Amino acid sequence: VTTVVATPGQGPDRPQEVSYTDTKVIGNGSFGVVYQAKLCDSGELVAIKKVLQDKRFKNRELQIMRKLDHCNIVRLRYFFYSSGDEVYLNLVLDYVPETVYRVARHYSRAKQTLPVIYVKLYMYQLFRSLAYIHSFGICHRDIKPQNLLLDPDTAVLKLCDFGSAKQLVRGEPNVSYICSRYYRAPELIFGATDYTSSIDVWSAGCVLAELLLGQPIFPGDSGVDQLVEIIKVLGTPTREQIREMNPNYTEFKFPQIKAHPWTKVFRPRTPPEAIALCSRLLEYTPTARLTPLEACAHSFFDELRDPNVKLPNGRDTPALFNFTTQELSSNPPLATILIPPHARI
Amino acid sequence: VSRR
Ligand SMILES: Cc1c[nH]c(-c2cnc(NCCNc3ccc(C#N)cn3)nc2-c2ccc(Cl)cc2Cl)n1
Image (cartoon, rainbow over all chains, first blue to last red):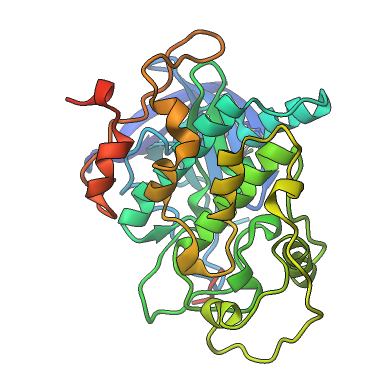
């Protein structure tokens, strides 16, 4: 049961003994393997992610987790190399009981859709997590509901799995084949190598539509079929839209397909402010897509800024307004909307 | 991802 190691942690340079037990496997995947454990000193639950190797690719997940401190991002407590094939790296992370994907599935299996209030809360904290990494120029590049940790009582969301994460710098190129296929932005389908962090915003728009539809909006069988799925809703891209996604890409004609009206994409009950926000996220043109802070300020979230807002269980909402100056870097003037009067000072 |  009990296991002991020495690791530095986030804050200092102070390797120290930490002991954990009751270890259980959570899952296997592209991220490696994640275990649950109890830290012996505090009794707190933790998640432990194990991954590697140099392979020919430039991983970055450490050096990104050490830089981040956000209530909507899972925190890195500790890390420690170990045996287990080759050496092994372990990241010790905050444990969170659920994922948005699992909770969205629980509603779908009951032929229920996730309540809008949870759609607003979950989507708002994701964009807030996105605004924070994007202020550092960092792009998550794998925004999918499986990577959205969630505490069901508090409705707190925590972005996780930064194993695809990269700090984008103009003029450096980046692989096009990145991001789970269903959430992959069209620029990536077109082979663009100069893409911005706007791809995460496209992915967040896929998550939003999925939370409204109860199933993924663009389930492609291939990268090429992913573009067909998008076209069936967005309709055929038109130059310059193709040009804005990939300036060097050229000949695409493709039968012209009329866009499906956005009101017909979603069930009739869907509130227009959710449909309208989605239209401003699922744009072909990356520059047309909203910034995360611009999404937070969207009217779809106005209910979260009301003074008389409570979770359906009656608990207070998680903190939504404790913005840092860094978090507001993209547009500090937006704070007047983002911070409602009752939350000021 | 990117190689190298
Ligand atoms: C096969 C498979 C794929 N995904 C899962 C899965 C299922 N259930 C849960 N529940 C959340 C448990 N709490 C957690 C989980 C992770 C972290 C962190 N970092 C913190 N807290 N989490 C995952 C999960 C989600 C993200 C990753 Cl990177 C890995 C896993 Cl195993 N199983």
